[PDB]
Image (spheres, rainbow, N blue to C red):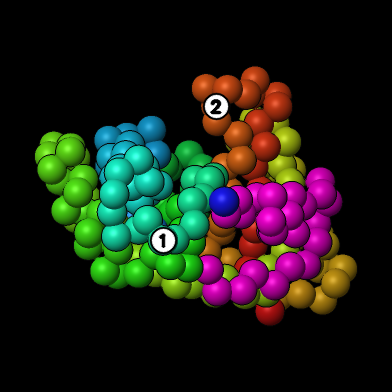
Amino acid sequence: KIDFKKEEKKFYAPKRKPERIFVPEMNFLMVDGKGDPDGEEYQKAVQSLYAIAYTIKMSKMGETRLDGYSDFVVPPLEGFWWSEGKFDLKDRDAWLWTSILRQPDFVTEEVLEWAKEVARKKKPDVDTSRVKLVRFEEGECVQMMHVGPFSEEVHTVAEMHQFMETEGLRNDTGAIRKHHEIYLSDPRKANPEKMKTILRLPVS
């Protein structure tokens, strides 16, 4: 059984200080969107992503074309974040994002198409049109574990920026190589003070 968090700790278990990391090509389900993540569009994006991810995962409970492949643990939700103009924490409506879930390498475009058809039958009211499969190499980054509320992220980002300066790294964060968060904690399960989120920023 594939478990990305356990098998690849370098990517999912950084320390609470900035470190360089090269993130190689990985396979993802992705949904692009816009606007405040407290809004409907983001809720639907995440719903759609999970509808497909769990269709693929829960395929194991029946006889399917996926019987021969390994089972897997559904990985943490992740997101890339940007904006057309200068990013503003006080203007969440202007946010642009991509919501993502890593997939096993065996998940191909044919598997995605199959999953969409299965999910349409099982949950006809969940639209999955925006779910795409993308193999993506994030590349050279700096990352750090952020423990605590999202509002305190500014301090973690500041440490990361300071590390970049000291190490002679260029900050590539923008529309192309994007600010990246990996949501290790479920806010239904973890006290705000105990939320774990990986922040990862692209460098050159």
Q: Position of residue 176 (x, y in %)?
A: 47, 72
- The part of the chain drawn in magenta is 2-26
**View extreme (right): residue:** 166
Element under disc 1: loop
Q: Is residue 5 magenta?
A: yes
Element under disc 2: loop
Q: Is residue 155 magenta?
A: no
Alpha carbons under labels 1 and 2: distance apart: 35 Å
Which residue is disc 2 drawn over?
A: 187
- Near-viewer residue (169 or 45): 45
* Residue 152 visible in the shown view: no
At x 52%, y 22%, the residue is 188
Against 3, residue 167 (above or below) is below
Q: Quadrant of the C terminus?
A: bottom right
At x 71%, y 42%, the residue is 146
- Near-viewer residue (157 or 192): 192
- Near-viewer residue (189 or 108): 108
Mark 1 or mark 2, which has the lower sequence index?
Answer: 1
Which residue is disc 1 drawn over?
A: 68
Against 133, residue 3 (above or below) is above
* Residue 122 in which image quadrant: top left
* Residue 183 in which image quadrant: top right
- Near-viewer residue (46 or 55): 55
Which kind of residue does numbered mark 2 sit on? Pro
At x 58%, y 66%, the residue is 173
Q: Position of residue 112 (x, y in %)?
A: 28, 61
Which kind of residue does numbered mark 1 sit on? Gly
At x 65%, y 58%, the residue is 200
Crowd class of label 1 (few under 14; some 14 to 19; many from 20; radius 10 Å): few
Q: Position of residue 36 (x, y in %)?
A: 37, 40
* Residue 89 visible in the shown view: yes
Q: Are marks 1 and 2 in contact (CB under 8 Å)?
A: no
